[PDB]
Image (cartoon, coloured by chain):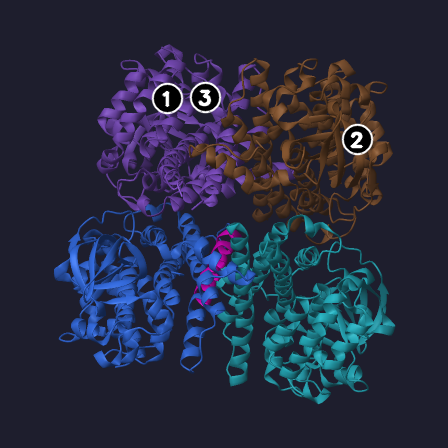
Chain colours: A brown, B purple, C cyan, D blue
């Protein structure tokens, strides 16, 4: 297999994942049958290092995947994007950590919650961690998890990063009763007095520096993309896919409807939505590609580009959502029924919107600072 | 010289053209200086056929040029784009028409007014043209002009296209007293009982077919580019350049302010305003130029351009204009009181874009119906 | 007892009604206790003729009632407005029809489905009625219904209006499973080969004519108000009400987070102002109309046109402001129990009616502005 | 003569002022002819106290008049509202200051520049005032001016207000070369070492407290009206008026194209949607802009006090009115297409004029919106 054949296989899955969207929403977590299928065609290998049988691929092709997934099932696209990018994150961890996860089984999955909703206290050999983390999309389908939060040594915050912990050392509290992305199963992770070895903590600082241990062995270009582009993009890409899905739905339904042998108003709003969605994607995937092309040539990623990515990325979410709102309003009465696909895309996108990577202001201030000749702050870049 | 060095030389014209902006406006048409500088650097040869010394370039580079020009002077960018693209249109005329225009002096320029404000009636060996055509940008700097309209036979139209007429067979009436694009000198061409030979008419139909006569000797891929993308983009590219100009102006001004205030307010909204406009401007340009390059790449590979792509180009192009103007308005508002001065560039960029917006190729509805119809399955 | 006291009494039901919102949503119809309480304080009497113990009130006070209800429970306010204006409509039917509905018990309620999803075929003594009408909000709580349709006389439509049919002659099909307005129970009404007497049909023409049989016995100025304002307003008023509900909900929660960001202040202020604007216009137009009727004057067509352009605008404004507050609410708004997402979901469901369509209203108004003649019958 | 009389008379001034519109722009200040006619119909007496022969009128009628004037000539509506309102502001100064201004000639006019671009230093019996104040609309037509700034006692700001200064003690610098409101002649005021006595300064705080001197002789309810409503509304009213002007320019032009295609034959829903939305939005700018003023005045005329929440609501609605007017004008102007680019097209003038007006400090949206949000949230509070 290679990157392109995995994409082809994913195309083939779309119709079945689509028909399952209701059931997916019902389960409040991905159906085992779709996760298995994904796993079987190689989706999770996509951004996985080749030392573990993976494809350590071009990041643009991976998001292009998630966009397809989200274009038939919001929750499927959302979880896939997030779980997949974890196999990219784990590659920046040092060999020891990687070994524990994929040693006996390379198709092992990791979930996460990067918001600092807990902490790890220094002991001999690493960390003693406690906290309750929420929103771990797809945690129901993973054997390990990351959790974000500071390192506290003798009181006070020294580092901030992610801790890697096994399913057996955290409880999963089912509190996923929300208005959108219902089937993401983004439950809550309870960590009590769990020791985590020093080789299962990765610093963001380290990642920024290109001194993350795992890079020695995993030297493919893709493992040097900035977290600030890679992570928020994992959030925006599926949302963009949701707009594509909402668009196709509405077009189908509006097509039959306007074959009655004029209605300029209906045409305009479809042309505008189509163009805004296209602009979202071009920018999002475009900044991703500009950065990977640079790394591929051995060159370095200038701050200006990372800042442009952040502002375009929050913007992409904005215009995907605005388009979906206009396509929803236009679908009229028949979009109100609990089964109607367009209303699902609309609910899902709005749920996704609350994710922190989507806060427009945060991202615009970073880009605004850079244009105005100001020192960087916000590390989410 | 090639396309790339012409692009490079145009960068070095930018500062002087910038400084000339007010003079340009006050003239109510382009200054001889600037027209001569563009000619000398080879700008007008960009889309000109090879057999005449032209570079028959990648259409995307021509448009990058117009963008840069318009980012310092709205009127220059607007005129340059329009008169430049006419060297493209003429390539499609059959050789004889070309010979009359370039045969003695290959640097000869042509203007146009494409909206149907007259007509040609069939007679022995051509047509009898009558009409009054407005909005001929840079007409004072051309010695031929295109005029658009139907060919009428015995009462009903039997064709539609462009008539190529020399300086001496039409009158220029100065009517350019407007709120924006004042330097464009977009005056009115008056044509009375003028005979045009058939080899100086060109059907739009004949361009779509690829039956247009000039195509035989002018074989480069650029000349297979669709009229429906080339002409509207010629209008959009400069409007987007103006948005770039507006942006740079507002950032230079506002930047000196946020710095300095950085020593004992905090105006997060000044940065939101700036991040949003740069994003929307980038998007306009990516789509506008993106569509150009997709089409050209197809042609370069001896492939054909699918109808759906041509319809995306139209929806994107009118949208591009819209993104630009909307972004310029936000920037203009954000510049506050200083932007009102007659000598502040941002109010010129703003008036210019709004004046450019009234062009037919920018009507959004008309383009959106086209893309909608295609989406919906309709004709 | 009068409209102001009914109004003040409605204030008291608000806390109970707000707390019942979730139970109302789960029930998929209004809980019996809320219908009972509304009947107790006299809400259904508000637009009802005096001969039936009704208050035949100034309609601005009725709509102000629905707004208050919708600000604590979107479904309650929606159902109350619609069922409540039905007592206005019946007053226009001739005396005998009112007799049959209210003579025995004046507290009897009526539901509707006005869209023409069936028809009435002329027969001996009246009509034979057939169809399946959807979206009958509050039908579970009514013992009669209106269904909209044409009158068919020998295969050709000769009239259009409403037929009034008793519970025993139609079936209620439970099909109400929706993203919002869950508590409205807008189920479907199945009507098979049902005879309706001539006196239980009212033409819309006759309602515009002022020849509706009921005006002889019910001469209060409120019954002379135009259907084109009254009906669409019973849809818009509650929606505006929901915006008020969403606003209060968001200010309360966000207000504590703050006693712990100018951005939050801006969203809230634009939202507050756009909501206020929507209400002022919607209720202003209704009040101006009634004032003329009450003075003995006629309503000019231009006021009616304005009512309609403002009415669909009020909805747009309300829904945009809700959309902004709901976004601002962020993560908390996602829990299935969050009141703000209910308002958000209820508002967008109400938007599909059907009478919030802006184009139709705006065409009516544009035509009038352009001096074009009245064509469309509104609604 | 009363306030309704003056209004009626202003109506018959409209066509002339409309006709003058272009001449006005080119002058870069209002024509003596206009100013003279406004004076003669009694426009400037509207908010002037009765002791000076003024009408001390219902301020809603005042703002209505500026709307009307601004609906035919933006500059004229702009200058008129601003200079007219100064007769209101002067009413709050000490009786002595009113005497100096209107003692001989009750029709004398005042201009202003209210932003702190200078300062007054405490000296015996008054202040020593220095500064360069820009943007003084209509100054070429006034013989007095207000200039705003803090009072500096021993090098520290200890109060804030307006200083009243006669023409002989300041220079009018001509610098008005702008893209819009060309005819307002909003030039610069230079004041160098000018003594201003105690009684020709008015603290904003004192206006708020109701301790301003003028209240001793001017008891009419209009003078209890808040500065934070009167001053910003004077900026917004004319702008809404410009929006009314553009609306009618557009409607009469567009109507031909739409009626012509009404049978043969293109249908044009877009054009009517666009006109319905603007009309509704302009109507909404006016309802709340004038409603807040009416609600305020209705309280004062009945001896009641104005609650802070109305003043805060007034401010959110006033900057919001400006915004709505400008968004609507933008849409109408775009829609009017190529004939609207002409130097003689009124709409392009309304468009440039409204966008010039927008830069005024009283229109900044965030400041007003922060005031209103603070109040909704409990936060402690100015305005203008």
Please give left or right for residue A241 compared with residue C259 in the image. right
> Looking at the image, which residue is at 32% across and 69% down?
D65
Foreground pick, A99 / B39: A99
Question: Which corner quadrant holds the C terminus of chain B?
Answer: top right
The image position of residue A64, as x and y in percent, is: 67, 27
Which mark, by number, is residue B59?
A: 3
Q: Is the magenta stretch mostly helix, strand or loop?
A: helix
Q: Which chain carries label 3?
A: B
C76 to the left or right of D362? right
Closer-to-camera residue (A88/C237): A88
Marks 1 & 3 on one chain: yes
Q: Distance between the residues labelled 2 and 1?
A: 74 Å
Q: Where is residue A192 in the image (x, y as percent from the top left)?
A: 80, 39
Give the Cα separation between the discs numbered 1 and 3.
Answer: 12 Å
Chain for numbered disc 1: B
**Looking at the figure, which quarter contains the N terminus of chain B?**
top left
- Image quarter for residue D124? bottom left
Q: Which mark is residue A195?
A: 2
Subunit under mark 2: A
Q: Say if C342 sits above or below C84 in the image.
A: above
Q: Is residue C139 left or right of residue D290?
A: right
Q: How far apart are marks 2 and 3 (CA)?
A: 62 Å
């Amino acid at each position: 297999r290679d990157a392109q054949s995995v994409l082809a296989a994913i195309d083939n899955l779309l119709p079945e994942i689509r028909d399952r969207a209701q059931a997916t929403e019902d389960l409040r977590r991905l159906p085992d049958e779709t996760v298995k299928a994904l796993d079987d065609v190689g989706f999770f290998t996509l951004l996985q290092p080749q030392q573990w049988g993976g494809l350590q691929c071009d990041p643009a092709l991976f998001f292009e995947a998630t966009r397809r997934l989200a274009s038939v099932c919001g929750s499927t696209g959302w979880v896939s994007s997030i779980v997949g990018v974890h196999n990219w994150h784990l590659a920046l961890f040092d060999q020891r950590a990687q070994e524990e996860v994929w040693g006996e089984d390379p198709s092992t999955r990791i979930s996460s919650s990067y918001a600092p909703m807990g902490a790890g206290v220094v002991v001999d050999g690493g960390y003693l961690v406690n906290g309750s983390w929420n929103w771990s999309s797809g945690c129901d389908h993973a054997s390990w998890t990351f959790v974000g939060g500071p390192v506290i040594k003798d009181g006070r915050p020294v580092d901030f990063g992610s801790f890697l912990i096994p399913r057996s050392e955290y409880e999963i509290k089912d509190v996923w009763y929300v208005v959108g992305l219902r089937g993401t199963g983004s439950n809550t992770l309870v960590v009590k007095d769990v020791f985590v070895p020093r080789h299962r903590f990765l610093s963001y600082k380290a990642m920024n520096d290109h001194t993350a241990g795992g890079l020695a062995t995993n030297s493919a270009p893709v493992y040097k993309m900035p977290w600030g582009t890679m992570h928020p993009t994992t959030i925006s890409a599926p949302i963009v896919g949701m707009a594509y899905g909402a668009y196709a739905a509405h077009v189908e339904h509006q097509g039959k409807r306007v074959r009655a042998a004029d209605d300029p108003f209906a045409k305009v709003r479809i042309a505008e939505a189509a163009s805004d969605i296209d602009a979202a994607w071009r920018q999002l995937i475009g900044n991703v590609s500009d950065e990977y092309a640079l790394l591929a040539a051995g060159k370095e990623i200038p701050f200006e580009l990372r800042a442009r990515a952040r502002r375009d990325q929050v913007r992409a979410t904005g215009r995907s959502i605005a388009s979906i709102d206009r396509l929803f309003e236009a679908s009229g009465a028949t979009a109100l029924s609990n089964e109607a696909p367009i209303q699902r895309f609309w609910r899902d996108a709005h749920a996704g919107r609350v994710h922190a990577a989507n806060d427009p202001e945060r991202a615009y201030v970073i880009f605004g600072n850079h244009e105005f000749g100001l020192p960087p702050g916000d590390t989410m870049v």
